[PDB]
Image: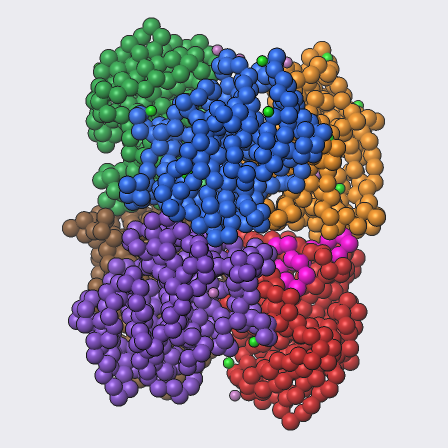
Chain colours: A brown, B purple, C red, D blue, E green, F orange
Amino acid sequence: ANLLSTCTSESGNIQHISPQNAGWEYVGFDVWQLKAGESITLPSDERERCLVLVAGLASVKAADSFFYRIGQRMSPFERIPAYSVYLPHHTEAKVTAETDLELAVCSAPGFGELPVRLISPQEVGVEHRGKGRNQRLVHNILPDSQLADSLLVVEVYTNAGATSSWPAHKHDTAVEGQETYLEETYYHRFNPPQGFCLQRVYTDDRSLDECMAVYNRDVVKVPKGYHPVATIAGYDNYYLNVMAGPLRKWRFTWEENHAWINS
Amino acid sequence: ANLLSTCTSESGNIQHISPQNAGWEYVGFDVWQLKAGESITLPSDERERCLVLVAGLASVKAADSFFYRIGQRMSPFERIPAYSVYLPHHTEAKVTAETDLELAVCSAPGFGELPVRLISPQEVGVEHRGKGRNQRLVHNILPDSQLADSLLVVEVYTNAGATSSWPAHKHDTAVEGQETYLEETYYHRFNPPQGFCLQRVYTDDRSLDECMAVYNRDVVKVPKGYHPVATIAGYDNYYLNVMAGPLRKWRFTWEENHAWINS
Amino acid sequence: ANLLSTCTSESGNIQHISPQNAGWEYVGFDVWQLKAGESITLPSDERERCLVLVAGLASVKAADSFFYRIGQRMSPFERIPAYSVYLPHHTEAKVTAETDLELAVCSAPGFGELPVRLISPQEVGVEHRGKGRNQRLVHNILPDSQLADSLLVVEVYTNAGATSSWPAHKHDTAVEGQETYLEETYYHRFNPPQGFCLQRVYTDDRSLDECMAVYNRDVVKVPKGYHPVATIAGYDNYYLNVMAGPLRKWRFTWEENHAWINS
Amino acid sequence: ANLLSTCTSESGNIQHISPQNAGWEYVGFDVWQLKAGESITLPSDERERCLVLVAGLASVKAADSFFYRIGQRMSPFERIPAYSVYLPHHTEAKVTAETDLELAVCSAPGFGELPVRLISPQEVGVEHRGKGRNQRLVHNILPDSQLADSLLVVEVYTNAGATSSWPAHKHDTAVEGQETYLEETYYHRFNPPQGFCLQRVYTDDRSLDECMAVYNRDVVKVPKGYHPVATIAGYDNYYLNVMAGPLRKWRFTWEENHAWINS
Amino acid sequence: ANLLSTCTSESGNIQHISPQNAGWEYVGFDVWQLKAGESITLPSDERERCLVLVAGLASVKAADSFFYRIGQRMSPFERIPAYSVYLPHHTEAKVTAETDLELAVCSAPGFGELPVRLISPQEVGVEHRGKGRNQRLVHNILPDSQLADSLLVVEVYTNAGATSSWPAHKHDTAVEGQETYLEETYYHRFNPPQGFCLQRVYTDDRSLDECMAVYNRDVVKVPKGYHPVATIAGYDNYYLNVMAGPLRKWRFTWEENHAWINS
Amino acid sequence: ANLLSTCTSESGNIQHISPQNAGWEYVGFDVWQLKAGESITLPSDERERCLVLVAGLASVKAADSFFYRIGQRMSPFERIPAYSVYLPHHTEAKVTAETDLELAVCSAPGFGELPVRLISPQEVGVEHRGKGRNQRLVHNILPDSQLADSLLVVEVYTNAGATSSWPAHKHDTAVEGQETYLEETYYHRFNPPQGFCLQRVYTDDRSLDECMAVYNRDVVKVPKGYHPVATIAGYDNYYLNVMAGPLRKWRFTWEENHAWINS
Ligand SMILES: [Cl-]
Ligand SMILES: [Cl-]
Ligand SMILES: [Cl-]
Ligand SMILES: [Cl-]
Ligand SMILES: [Cl-]
Ligand SMILES: [Cl-]
Ligand SMILES: [Cl-]
Ligand SMILES: [Cl-]
Ligand SMILES: [Cl-]
Ligand SMILES: [Cl-]
Ligand SMILES: [Cl-]
Ligand SMILES: [Cl-]
Ligand SMILES: [Cl-]
Ligand SMILES: [Cl-]
Ligand SMILES: [Cl-]
Ligand SMILES: [Cl-]
Ligand SMILES: [Cl-]
Ligand SMILES: [Cl-]
Ligand SMILES: [Cl-]
Ligand SMILES: [Cl-]
Ligand SMILES: [Cl-]
Ligand code: NI
Ligand code: NI
Ligand code: NI
Ligand code: NI
Ligand code: NI
Ligand code: NI
Ligand code: NI
Ligand code: NI
Ligand code: NI
Ligand code: NI
Ligand code: NI
Ligand code: NI
């Protein structure tokens, strides 16, 4: 299975993951690397979006509003929450780079009537998950406790020598009250930039079992199974995750052999 | 090519095959394993459906009707026809498990105006196909001689030591008066339950040639080519098949090397 | 990655490439091999089409018109431009084979209001590209300088011992003013007919690097990367290409190591 | 894994399996298809051999012995035991085809001082193994109860439909008093000749799990795991097996899930 | 590539890696899991050996020497050096399990005239390599500064989270004064036992790039390239390595991008 | 299959192909990239060798012979024959680089008593094979009409565009008077150096069918089948081939479909 998508270029639409090229039904994930002064226009269509400023400042025109010079961090490694913008479906938007800009466009099916809204770093829930070699900084950009039709968005910091997305969990089957089907994308970053991590996507029966050396700005698709991330000594890791499915609830099942790591 | 889809769980939506994850255009196939008292709701959308009760009893609310305790067999290995329900498109339906229930939801594009209808075991055409090591019990749940927009549904019993879907046939190309393009899914069952069969999906030129060890509740996708099933001594086999394409007619071509087995 | 699609049959719809089975978003490509007197009907839908007569004569009924015995060449190897027909979306059309007919149906998303139009061999721009072992005859059936919503269509002749689609170029990423995302299909032909060529689809990082022995009437899909064609001594090559993407402009980037071959 | 070796030609040394090309330590297997009057010379080396006359008549000169026009069956499908000649190591041999000849040369390490000997039909143990979809005819050409340094040779007849090398067994690990490491080759034949069977080689953890479609005169290598053969309606099967390892004792372990098929 | 070898059984010769099955020239690695009172005999041949008592107590008879009840640790996770016995070539040896025993037999070509010798904990060099997420305990059982014809043997302890065989190094090419060709095996163990690590074997050009999920008692073969081990939170790792080549000198090259981690 | 071996380094033993790592029985091929003043020593063993000076000057000491500063061309692309030295088995040799040196060591089993000899340009048969897109320069360094126990060595120059090892031939089966089994290695070079060619290794049944993109100093292994080389406009190609088998005679069979290209 080919779950790894390496960047296609250095500038422009460096990552383009769609339901059509991912072989799935809900999640889309795009990254644009723009120079100061450049713009993109997002269309009025049947998809809701979450614009995540990974690095740099931007101005956004949408609905009847103008949002000027949103963003703050110049690197995701500043460890301060991303500035994001929620766009409902049927919303054309123009995004202009105020500085050089690394922009994530998270997409999923849209059908509701929520308004355009800003998700500033102060609206992002911050949590420190796990203990020891399992410690991670989590920024809940768009959790299931906040409003959206489909999208669930999170960014996670895993320092070199820690394991994250671990103990192994899956969200690949609708099992009422236990688990939901949620497609998931990982957009990875490293500090220093030449680093890599090892991500493994696997099922209990191992019918799917793929390990991948993931480098800076690579995407990993998670269509099913467990999906832990093992970082490498010397290279701090960051990832931006998008999830969506038929039911917007994060319900997962832990792999039974490793569930004791939560105790 | 990955044509085999093993069950993702023991309960809930254990099989979910869609045009999007199958890499094709028409056929969808879902299996739900429900405990007595649990329900699912099927949406009003652009897909027609055939609900097939593989094992157990169910109640269905659809259109202006209530169908109570439909089904009979508690195992597909009773060798009595499944109870099924035809749902046209734009038909919301609620299915409640009266007993523990193994429910197949067969789907394809819907566009007509046929009514909701019951397909009881007495409406299922029963035929005994082949002679010797080629003998099989066939239950024509929804054949091309019965009404539906797209769906063709059949279940077949192949006793241990027989070959079925054989002599090799294909339905992967529109060839006027000879063959139709029909995507096909296989949902396999074994008695005793720990068994397997060997299914081979292959083209004449062998550009596609994949053999698979298929276990209990596994799905095989047939996007093209010949697709025979070789059963194993000691393990009786059952499969539930769904087909659909642009033209709802079962027209196939026999592999010429093995066509003499029909003589 | 499986980028090669060999013919499924000798007659009827011998090639059927869709966004759904290609794992992409825009381009569809069909070939029909029809005997004199046979017909097909193309539907009124949301796709625009370019009918390309690869070999043989046809009559077309579309919109309020009847086009009788269009075509001329009985083989693509006559090296005279194909006769083609542009069909906008929402246009049902009936195509009848006047002689035995090899018909290419090129498709992409349609949304405009252009009329049905004939593209006769006299409307096709003819150019001789390259020098020496890089020489090729190019027929611009439907270039970006002519009108269509999405479709770009070209046919190219590469004589045995020449390389084409070379120096290596890619059109797989939206990079403003430099490159566009364009899915591309290749439909290959050989003279004598038992020949083959070697086509390689690869990225700069080699995460994708697939070489393929392509035979008569085979299709190669190009979802991303560089995609040169190396012909074989004794076997002249022909290919028919279809491209489409979000922006109908042919903008590509040359692989830097081989760009000097243009000098 | 690559366990299937198809014939490289119709005449001469059509099968050549060596420890060097098999990725293992002991077993060699060669097939020679000779016309009446042709000969081959086997060298004096460190390997013992068992020359199996699969079909046709041959004369064999080795050491102080000459065997004139030995053989009987003109096809393995006569279901009568083969003639064979055991050759110790350091024994040059000349084999002359008296009729058209299909000759199997089974080889393994030699170190002893056994004499050259004929293994006529009268020295072959004939047995019927299993009941029903499991009943095969077995010819023990060179069992562990007869003399050789390393070689174990058997031929088996599996009628169309039936499963052989079943219930699944393995002989891939030295487990004192339970199992021995024995490399194994299968040389397959079909009646009628255009047939195939499905052979699956797999381990308990499925780290190796390969199913292959086996045609006439193909060889399957079994370096480890379970290795059952599933035959296809209409096509009777035959195979000639060679085994060897560090300990010349046929000790195997049954896969636990299917062991009940022996009771 | 197929670099992972999982255990073939729970008892007996659970690991058997040979130059013939590894696709290389020097290194052999065997593991024997024996019950108290069981024995094995190692042959007199052209290979030298290093018998490593991974866990448990053993007696060893070889040439004019008898070692009674050597060993100490009942688990490799006691973090105390193993007892080992060096055997020159042409030296038959009998190993008797005094307790349940996990025995590693490390082999390589032998040509010299060194005597049989005990390598007790007092002859094992103990060192701590690296700082933080990089700090491992290393036991030099048989380094290049001690006597053997070919064999180099080391065991390493990597605590959960940490990265070992890192910064990435290779020893796959004879480069005078810089690097030697050395085949390498890894025999992995976990505490608790149900754990895994992720090991990646890769070259600078990524022509080889394999990441594998390694479980308890699995073997990884390193025929060339970089080969770091990434451990997982909760699961401590241990591995026993064997190396050999034409020149018995441990000379390696660091991957240039990660060499800074040594400063 | 894995038939391509890319260089492991820029200096030293950049190519090391052995029967053990190639999965075959006879051919060994090594390349050494040495700086002026460096030396290597070839051992006294059971292999005969042909030392080919691909580029640069070398002195060779072997048995009672010393060859001082032999060689001439500083690049294979000078299109003048190489100097080579034939070494029988049991012959230790010292090779000193007099200038920077690219040295090929071709090896195969040795058993005879031929003397050490120089193969100077005057002993190399020069021939031009084929017409047009098929015309190559061939240097028969060590043909079957010259003396050696096993080795067959040739170098071929294929100008950009042209196809070589074409029409397709195979030498993979002993067929008396028609074909011999001969393993074959290709050591490729390009001018300019950043180029590539496409080489396809395939059998008549396509059970093996591998096309690879070959770059400067890469090696392709041909264990069986047809093996043509398709060059790319702008990049001239060179390759040095080594062959050996049980019978030192170059006998091949042409693929029937392309045999007409010889007329
Ligand atoms: Cl949309
Ligand atoms: Cl996490
Ligand atoms: Cl739920
Ligand atoms: Cl729908
Ligand atoms: Cl059937
Ligand atoms: Cl029809
Ligand atoms: Cl449409
Ligand atoms: Cl071109
Ligand atoms: Cl642009
Ligand atoms: Cl005798
Ligand atoms: Cl007789
Ligand atoms: Cl059997
Ligand atoms: Cl035993
Ligand atoms: Cl001693
Ligand atoms: Cl002691
Ligand atoms: Cl280390
Ligand atoms: Cl050195
Ligand atoms: Cl001499
Ligand atoms: Cl000279
Ligand atoms: Cl040639
Ligand atoms: Cl010959
Ligand atoms: Ni709406
Ligand atoms: Ni997740
Ligand atoms: Ni409707
Ligand atoms: Ni079918
Ligand atoms: Ni419209
Ligand atoms: Ni292109
Ligand atoms: Ni002897
Ligand atoms: Ni066996
Ligand atoms: Ni000795
Ligand atoms: Ni190492
Ligand atoms: Ni000798
Ligand atoms: Ni050749």
Residue E41 % position (x, y): 34, 17
- Which of these two is toward me, D206 or E27? D206
Please state if F6 lies on the left or on the right of E239 as rendered.
right
Look at 66% across and 79% down and name the residue there: C38
> For residue D53, what is the image quadrant?
top right
Name above or below for residue B136 compared with residue C245.
above
Q: Which residues are magenta?
A: C212-235
Task: State which quarter of the image contains the C terminus of chain C.
Answer: bottom right
Picture layout, residue A36 above or below residue E154: below
Residue name at image x 61 percent, y 54 percent: C212
Residue sitting nearer the eye, D148 or F251: D148
Indicate left or right for E182 with B59 as reference.
right
Q: Quadrant of residue F2?
A: top right
| Residue F24 among those drawn in magenta | no
- Give coordinates of residue F177: x percent, y percent: 75, 33
Tell me what residue is drawn at x 76 percent, y 28 percent. F144
At which x and y percent is residue A40?
47, 75
Name the residue rendered at 25%, 86% in the picture.
B65
